[PDB]
Amino acid sequence: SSHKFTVVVLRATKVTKGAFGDMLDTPDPYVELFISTTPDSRKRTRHFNNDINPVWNETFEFILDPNQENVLEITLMDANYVMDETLGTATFTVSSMKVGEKKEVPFIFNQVTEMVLEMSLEVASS
Ligand SMILES: [Ca+2]
Ligand SMILES: [Ca+2]
Image (cartoon, protein in one colour):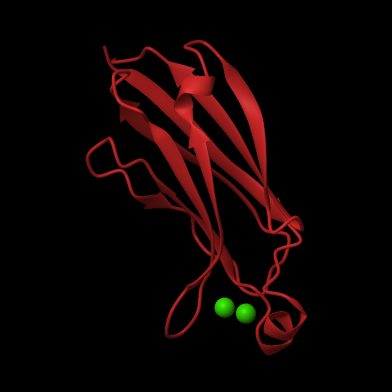
């Protein structure tokens, strides 16, 4: 049928570009979501200036087809003046979740920065 996949982009901790990159520019972070198997899905949070432990608490909704191999692509970004830098990329295969389930999935980027997401899967179609 059609499922409502809710992603709450909660927070990240110890966002870093490395020692040198952080001395040039303290990360100005945001998260970007993308699920290629659903129409205009690219979504993203607001960025925070010079914040290595950003708290977004932003809720995103994706209407998915359960026949597709739906993989949530999560990118931790740094807002820059010329070109935003991708500090890391994670994938979340929605198959791992079942309708009715709601769970916290933490992702670790570069074995240093933790990004916490809350996922929810429902059968929904109001
Ligand atoms: Ca900055
Ligand atoms: Ca920046």
